[PDB]
Image (cartoon, rainbow, N blue to C red):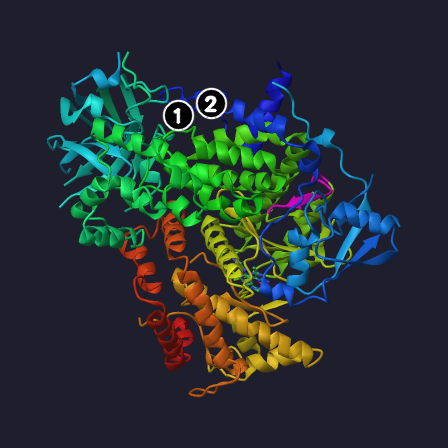
Amino acid sequence: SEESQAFQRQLTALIGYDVTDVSNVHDDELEFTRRGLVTPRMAEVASRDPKLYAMHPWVTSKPLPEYLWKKIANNCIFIVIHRSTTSQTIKVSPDDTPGAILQSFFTDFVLRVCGRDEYLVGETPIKNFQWVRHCLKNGEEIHVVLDTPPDPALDEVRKEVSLWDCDRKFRVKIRGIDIPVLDLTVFVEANIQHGQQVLCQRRTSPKPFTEEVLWNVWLEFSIKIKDLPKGALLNLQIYCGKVQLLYYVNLLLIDHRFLLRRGEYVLHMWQISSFNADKLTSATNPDKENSMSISILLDNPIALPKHMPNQLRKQLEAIIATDPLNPLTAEDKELLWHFRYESLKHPKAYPKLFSSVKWGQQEIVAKTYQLLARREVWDQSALDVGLTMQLLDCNFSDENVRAIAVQKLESLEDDDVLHYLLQLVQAVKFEPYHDSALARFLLKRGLRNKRIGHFLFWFLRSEIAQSRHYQQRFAVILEAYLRGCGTAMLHDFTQQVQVIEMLQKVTLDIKSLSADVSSQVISQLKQKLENLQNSQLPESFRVPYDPGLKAGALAIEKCKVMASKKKPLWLEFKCADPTALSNETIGIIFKHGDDLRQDMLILQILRIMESIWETESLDLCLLPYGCISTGDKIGMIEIVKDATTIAKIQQSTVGNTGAFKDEVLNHWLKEKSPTEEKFQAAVERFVYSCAGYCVATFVLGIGDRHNDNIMITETGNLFHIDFGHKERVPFVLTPDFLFVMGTSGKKTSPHFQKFQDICVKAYLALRHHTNLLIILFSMMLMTGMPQLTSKEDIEYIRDALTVGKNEEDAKKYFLDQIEVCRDKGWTVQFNWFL
Ligand SMILES: COc1ccc(Nc2ncc(CN3CCN(S(C)(=O)=O)CC3)cc2-c2nc(C)nc(N)n2)cn1
């Protein structure tokens, strides 16, 4: 109907890509994927409890850490409950279920966290609600309101010849290449591929490079048609010449219906700007009028069916015992495959084991599926995310192998999904087909949970906007999601897209008026911001990086354009919630010109490090602020309240010179403390903050930073910013940081001795997750950071995390690192000036 068509116009606007479109396809896969996702969509929409879905109790089921236990008033917490305005505080024990606390009060209505769309409902103890764990973390009082539970009717949705019996060698005709606009010899290269593994390869003869080049030649491969494994790609590449890769493109050999690929294809190609997610894509270049294209012929009803010695033991164990960046040699691979069944008893052998399979060999693949048919130990094992992630990366392309990882993901609690969601979304870039267990998993987990679903939207939306390589796929996943989240959430997303689009318009305009930063330009900002205040910016919108917060009208006076050379918008909003117990504005930086996905990744890895540290009862008070990529080169950043940079603290005392002074920071910290209890706690928070950032930035290899890119709160919380962008330094430990701790150049201190004692505990704790961090780091680089995609860059983290080396020796490596920051002093900061 037409009702279905205005709604399609709406979905398209929410995604920021026209799904129904067919200008950039060469088959029906994306359309097949839309239909195939209807079932998982509906099966989740129908089965989800409408009551718990409307209130999304953000609950964890982890042990409440040792650091938050011994910060309690004897198994009792104070919850302040609010009627109209006035309130009654109630004593409550960590085990008191929410519905039972209502009985404790009444001596149906629901509890909603004052100021937020966050509910304390369902059958979990209150110590298992993240909001509560946050209040304790930041030593604060749990304020809640007696509210009427939201109507689940708002969540309602608008109801809508066998291949193995073929011994032919694989051939492909290269008709030629056409380039609209342009002397050096050119050739086409053709690969049969599975993952990264090039199974078989063929070049053509080099011809003179002109607007059109024709070959009309058959390329016979040595691989047989029956040996082609599902997921196999034809990778066509074009070099010229000591040569250079110019354009590349890919084609699935076995399509989504299990059929061998036949007929004519006129594929549009991508240009090189090297492990890249993009280099694996089944998508062809949309830019018809500017791009190179290859023309090919396939002629081969062909569908695929659906079917020890002590030293060796030691050699095998040592192979299982290595990191995921250690290259397996031929001896290793031949050993793993032979001792296949021993290797299946060890969950950690799996990544290595399935990297030992020869996929260009039908009967070996068959044997591998028999091996998966008998995977009892894997199916029973206690889930490791690091092992699971390893099997969803680029090294694996077999749908069944990848499906054993997704299987393990099914058992993740919703809280743990949010922790890994970003990388899981990125992991979709390694799936051969648009419809996969993983896609379905994300699809349903987002549909089951309003929070996961919120972030899924922005994660996918972000990729759709700044990746031609995967927009089509993600777009199909997002449409499938939005068709299930419900009119309630669809309307939230709408307002949010409305706001960021309006803001971008203002940003683009203001950027043009500048060159440094004027003050009359700020008047033109405040001008156009008022122009939007009535028509037609919606009263209130959810904050993309913090979906609990509803932001209302702008604080126009407080809005400015930043001193940066990409002119970000410093913005502040009223909180739209009348029940909000404060008057603090919501501070958002709105930035155009940088692709923020990179900052997203680092900050997410930072949250992972936190949760890792929670398992070891540590807490290092990092500030991984909100950061959402919302469009093509636009996003928003959470402004951390009461925070100034290190550089500005120097730029104010010493002056705009550069002759830095040690004392300045401690004095700065003292001028901001009401008591000595509030100064030492502030110094204490600096002891962790700094130690947290020191460790983390060193492992990630982003430690060496300009001191204007490090900020501090007035409560002692140090934190790095702007992960967007000669002799070296590991991290940033300056004589002013060391002053706060006590040291004066070459001494020790009551706190400094604790600094190293917290750093090492932190460094070694991350080291217990070497595998996970390695795979996170690599996926970060492969899917999010194309500027640094060499093997040299990934092998940094092997050195940084000191693989193989035992604990005590690695401790000494880290202690040496701190003792390089002592040696270097200020020669780091100083050198940036010119
Ligand atoms: C990835 O892009 C960005 C951009 C900005 C930030 N954050 C900040 N960047 C710079 C500053 C320093 N700033 C200089 C300009 N002046 S001015 C006169 O133009 O208003 C304000 C202070 C601060 C931040 C920043 N970042 C966060 C996350 N919080 C806070 N409080 N501050 C992080 N990432």
How many residues crowd around disc 2 within 10 Å: few (fewer than 14), some, or many (20 or more)? few
12 left or right, relative to 325? right
For badge 2, the amino acid type reads Asp
Helix, strand or loop at mark 2: loop
* 203 in relation to 57, above or below: above
* 496 in relation to 482, above or below: below
541 left or right, relative to 614? right
Residue 543 belongs to the span the image colors magenta: yes
Q: CB of residue at label 2: within 8 Å of ligand 1? A: no
Foreground of the two, 463 or 41: 41
Kindly identify which numbered label has been placed on residue 21: 2
Asked whether residue 247 appears in the rendered view, the answer is yes
Magenta extent:
535-544
How many residues crowd around disc 1 within 10 Å: few (fewer than 14), some, or many (20 or more)? some
Task: Tell me whether circle 1 and circle 2 mark residues in contact (CB < 8 Å).
Answer: yes
Q: Please tell me whether the stretch drawn in magenta is mainly helix, strand or loop.
A: loop
Kindly identify which numbered label has been placed on residue 213: none
Alpha-carbon span between mark 1 and mark 2? 8 Å
Foreground of the two, 253 or 785: 253
